Image (cartoon, rainbow, N blue to C red; front, side, top):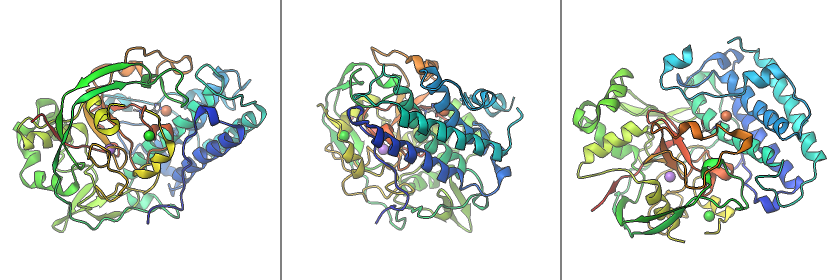
Length: 444
Ligand SMILES: C[N+](C)(C)[C@@H](Cc1cnc[nH]1)C(=O)O
Ligand SMILES: [Cl-]
Ligand SMILES: [Fe+3]
Ligand code: NA
């Protein structure tokens, strides 16, 4: 039916974060990332940076482990680290504007970084077993460091999965039980649905009993006018029509910045398509397969907007407030079990046909607002009123309130943890590739 053999534990309310439940959730966070890292066949592949805007894979093998250690030291739950050189080397990731910036380090051996991981795992597990979990946990409790570490690791499962997908298939091995969604399927008609206007409140209250990142908090009331939105995410088959109507070759659908990006990278189609013998194949995590015509297309923001340009007629993307209104209405009590109703949390090992998951239609009538692939939004990443950086990670989001990052919401098939729930806010530079697609909007 769907992926079952590789299983991801649902997140836990801070009022239920018992020592036993957290041990299980920590072990699961870490085992999942181990399964992903073990899919690289040859240790020399760890010195490749398959995405030219991100670090070599060796860095991501050590990074999630160093992050836990650094934050437990900062709250004084650990009195010393495991390797101070590695805790520096693996500390900070990257967000360059171009490949040259990043290109401009002696990495350790792969076996030395696995050793570091295994030692860190045992040190953290002992902290967990030796600390009292006085419920409830909260943002001024030292164990917030541990909750932050587990979510950071699950976020890096998702962003590392995109790096492994950019390696040649011959360099990776599919883990036992990895299961893609059914792919045969021509898409259904993608109808425009009227979403009735109303008021939404964005943000998260300080004492909400769920872990979250600083940029999730605050309070913003927004009056949202009615709008039309496509009931499905734009599919591979819809986007193939744009390609066949010279979408990548027509300047008027683009703008100068996005056209420059397209030309510089010689782009003729979405990143994970290849044209051979008269037809497109598609690169799933570990295998090439015939293009799944009814799955959501995966594009960066530039490509999403070019398709909007081809549609014409004021076609555009949703704002953050518009997505929230469509997904959650005007209400809200999170029900964590509802994550099972969407293509989230490794329900599948890939995107799914739009509409296949029959529980995934929001009350507004739109399908896969939650799950399947993130959806891009026409919204510069920005703080909500009441935003405050957290002492444990002051630079988490504030550097990126710079009008150079667009938002995306709702989670993908690969998304885990509190990132699958209502409050998480995601953001990327508009040229970046994620497990991410879009739907189209018109005012009238
Ligand atoms: C919020 N995104 C997903 C854009 C972040 C998450 C993150 C990882 N390590 C620190 N923050 C990113 O990938 O830079
Ligand atoms: Cl919910
Ligand atoms: Fe990180
Ligand atoms: Na979505």
